[PDB]
């Protein structure tokens, strides 16, 4: 199974989960305060692990890029933290965001004179440090994809503890406040103005669906601000659509490069034929955020984040996602299919990725990059099979016409998994968080073989076959 | 953890388990008849899998040696099947084996004229075919260790079905018949006379302890001839000691190379301090076969086959090996230590190998080669940890003085595991037994890195740490 000559192999990172770990890298944000919050820790809503004990990529990026380059990687999708670049509010620096009566952003203008007003309140040292990180990769002749938003917001934008206690009208309320979108536009323009020379492709945001659904509906997730409101979820979703559009327009003012979005795509399956039509509607609804962006002519490419599936059946006269399949499988166990489940309880289901890419190709006809795919597997028992089987899924979808430009694993290294902390280890490379030392897992060597040869060679082909990891 | 420049890395094979699989390779022996026996299959004593559906190394050796060479291996210990070389009886060809009154072989002479008598009744085509196999490896500049006996006997030597039914006085009875030793001596001389130019080091036999203990005591093992007699086990043991001594003397008639023995060494541990002295006695007794050979000045080197441990405690006023540890752990599960157990139920216990090598060094002060070490692991979930952790054990023992010359994994490929059949897969390389195709496992890539660099490099060092595979 050979990939095209220019098909990219690499990995993705985020600021919050990778940067901190060593002195001089701490930065406050909503997510910082959230994971440090004593109530959240004591209730078990978050793990008690803290991101400032993480892999210290802020300091150690050159060494990680060395590992990446030796694994045959030629593309990295990374992040830039708003909370770092603008630690103080930008509200008083006015720009032109034009909206229609329905609240759609129709145009933006952040003139050069305003970029210079922004410089004076930005942390330019942090901006230059990001340049050092990105340039260290770029100078090796490699591709860099910069994703503008990967969940943490500045605290002057969102104070989630205050929102959960007093309500969103009483405190800075994140994506529930219209003006957050306008401040994000200023940030997007600022970043593009300065960093376009280091960036090959842009993404406005990562997994906005996770932000709004987990923050305001699925509270067991332990995402900020964690108060239940379907109206709030809808408002944050609406605002995040506009944040994409504004940011797209902001970037295009200062860049000719492609601008896409990175999205969480579960594959949705019916347990039986009778539920097929209902599940087809659930797919449409679940992916509608992307559909909207594509339909407005505001997507040049799609970043596909794929990890697992959801399987649907009836429970008490209602169609629901079922325990024992997909993301709802037993941690460290097996799905009801017999497929192994990751340390996170996510079923190994590469068929989902093949189905998904064919569906997305047909739906949007856009270039796609697999921007995340991986598994929580602290001993590397299953990752090699996960890696090769999902890469074969991508190959198979490409043969049926999907325009896939690369595959980025989640991730190069273990990192801080949000409310779960460090116990979910997604790396091709193990990190000792006490020493910051990096150690290869065997999956890393498998990756290197495939990436260097641009192909799943026949000697590694059996790693796509899940027979010997599947029960019964 | 760097090994010495001439420390050897490689693998081991046996005739019965590897050779057969494709037309033209089938050969009769006691073990052939045993595994084909309808009663044994129906009772579940053997698996019903048949060796003639195996990896077909008789035909495919050049392709497996290619894999081995690319994995950085420079040594193979292989076999030669007595049942192939002498398919008809050799009894009428007389030689001089001198014994003392206590039954010890004091000298052997198999003159050149008698070697030529033997040629006329040998299967010389099989001998030449073995030469093609060994030479294919040797021609690459690599080391070959030839082991003369790896369990199957000619049927004219042993008819195990008839022995189990009618008793050893009523049929050819294998190592219960004194003359088997004399016939083995003829074989050993024949082999050395012809093949010494292809052989770097000799072994007379592999795991003689398994032959006598499993065939005559531990009948649940499904080893031939499978009738219970402590007296028989003692007689087979005594005869196998003499077979080693006879073969050593035979080989030395036609070779200047080192002659050793390959032995199964379980590491024995007390569950608690109160059982320590009893376990020390159990070690002495369990290894006494090797102690005898060394004490007679008939061992130039020791082949250490190490897989796991046995842990001892009191049960019903008796000290016994305990369920839930070592070789007596749950298949596919965990030992009571929390360590993972292989598909065979054998606890991952690298400390055992370190302890063993130090013990053997002190006991015998001989050069040692790890001639087997591996695990039944059909999806490679645990093998990489098993491989690196046991290699670190070897390194650690060498640092304390053990004279270890190389490490040979069991094995390069999946193969026929005796009474268990194909269900126990010990390969760095997976074999599809229907197609005979070989596929690398990630542990093979790990092995390649270590072998090519003569060291466990720091990036692979965490594979020696069993924390993330060990429960609670």
Image (tube, coloured by chain):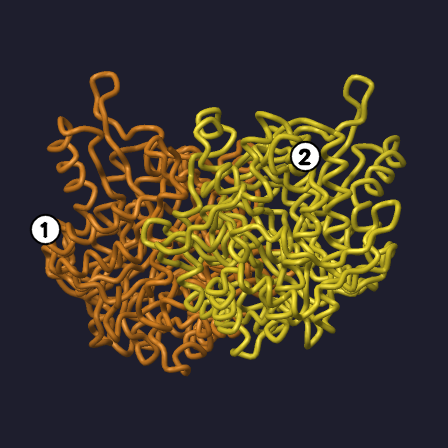
Chain colours: A yellow, B orange
Question: Do marks 1 and 2 share a chain?
Answer: no
Q: Distance between the residues labelled 1 and 2?
A: 73 Å
Q: Which is more toward the observer, B407 or A253? A: A253
Q: Residue at x 64, y 53 (%)?
A: A465
Question: How crowded is the residue under tag 2: few (<14 C-alpha within 10 Å), some, or many (20+)?
Answer: many
Rendered view: B73 above or below B148: below
> x, y percentage for residue A373?
62, 53
Compare residues A274 and A256 and report the one nearer the observer: A256
Q: In this view, does B191 lie to the left or right of A201?
A: left
**What residue is pinned by disc 2?**
A325
- Tell me what residue is drawn at x 26 percent, y 75 percent: B6
Q: Where is residue B84 in the image (x, y as percent from the top left)?
A: 45, 63
Q: Left or right: where does residue B353 sit relative to residue A54?
A: left
Name the one closer to the observer, B39 or B389.
B389
Chain bearing tag 1 is: B
Whether residue A444 sits left or right of residue A433 in the image: it is: right
Which image quarter holds the N terminus of chain B?
Answer: bottom left
Q: Position of residue B190 (x, y in %)?
A: 32, 71
Mark 1 vs mark 2: give the one in front. Answer: 2
Where B87 sits versus B158, above or below? below
Q: Is residue A337 visible?
A: yes
Depth order, front residue of B23/A111:
A111
Q: Residues within 10 Å of mark 1 (few under 14, many from 20)?
A: few
Q: Is mark 2 on a helix, strand or loop?
A: loop
Q: Which mark is residue B101?
A: 1
- Residue B117 picture quarter: bottom left
- Residue B91, image x and y in percent? 34, 60
Which of the numbered marks, if any, corresponds to residue B237? none
């Amino acid at each position: 199974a050979k990939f095209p000559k220019n098909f990219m192999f690499g990995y993705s990172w985020s600021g919050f989960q990778f940067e901190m770990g060593l002195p001089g890298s701490e930065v406050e944000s909503d997510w910082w305060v959230w994971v440090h919050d004593k109530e959240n820790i004591a209730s078990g809503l978050v793990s008690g692990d803290l991101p400032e004990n993480g892999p210290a990529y802020w300091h150690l990026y050159k060494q990680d890029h060395d590992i990446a380059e030796k694994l045959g990687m030629d593309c990295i999708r990374g992040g830039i933290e708003w909370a770092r670049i603008f630690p103080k509010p930008t509200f008083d620096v006015k720009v032109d965001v034009e909206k229609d009566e329905e609240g759609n952003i129709i145009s933006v203008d952040v003139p050069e004179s305003t970029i210079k007003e922004l410089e004076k309140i930005a942390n330019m040292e942090a901006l230059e440090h990001y340049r050092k990180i990105y340039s260290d990769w770029k100078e090796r002749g490699k591709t860099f994809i910069l994703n503008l938003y990967h969940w943490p917001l500045p605290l002057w934008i969102h104070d989630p503890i205050a929102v959960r206690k007093l309500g969103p009208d009483a405190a800075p309320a994140g994506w529930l406040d219209e003006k957050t979108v306008v401040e994000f536009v200023k940030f997007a323009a600022f970043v593009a103005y300065h960093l376009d020379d280091l960036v090959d492709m842009w993404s406005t945001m990562n997994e906005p669906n996770v932000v709004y659904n987990q923050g305001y509906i699925n509270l067991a997730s332990g995402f900020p601000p964690g108060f239940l409101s379907f109206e709030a979820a809808e408002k944050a979703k609406f605002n995040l659509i506009q944040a994409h559009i504004g940011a797209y327009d902001a970037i295009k003012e200062y860049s000719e490069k492609s601008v896409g979005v990175i999205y969480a795509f579960a594959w949705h399956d019916p347990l039986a034929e009778e539920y097929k039509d209902e599940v087809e509607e659930i797919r449409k609804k679940d992916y509608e955020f992307v559909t909207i962006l594509h339909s407005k002519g505001k997507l040049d490419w799609i970043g596909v984040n794929y990890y697992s599936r959801l399987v649907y059946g009836a429970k008490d006269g209602h169609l629901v996602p079922l325990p024992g399949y997909g993301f709802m499988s037993e941690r460290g166990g097996f799905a009801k299919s017999g497929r192994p489940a990751s340390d996170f309880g996510w079923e190994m289901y590469p068929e989902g990725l093949e189905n998904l890419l064919k569906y997305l190709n047909n739906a949007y006809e856009l270039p796609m990059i697999i921007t995340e795919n991986g598994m929580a597997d602290a001993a590397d028992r299953y990752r090699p099979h996960y890696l090769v089987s999902h890469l074969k899924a991508v190959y198979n979808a490409m043969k049926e016409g999907a325009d896939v430009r690369g595959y980025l694993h989640w991730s190069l290294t273990d990192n801080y998994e949000w409310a779960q902390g460090f116990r979910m280890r997604f790396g091709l490379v193990y990190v000792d968080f006490e020493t910051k030392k990096r150690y290869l897992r065997p999956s890393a060597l498998v990756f290197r073989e495939i990436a260097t040869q641009k192909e799943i060679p026949e000697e590694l082909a059996h790693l796509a076959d899940l027979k010997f990891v599947t029960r019964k």
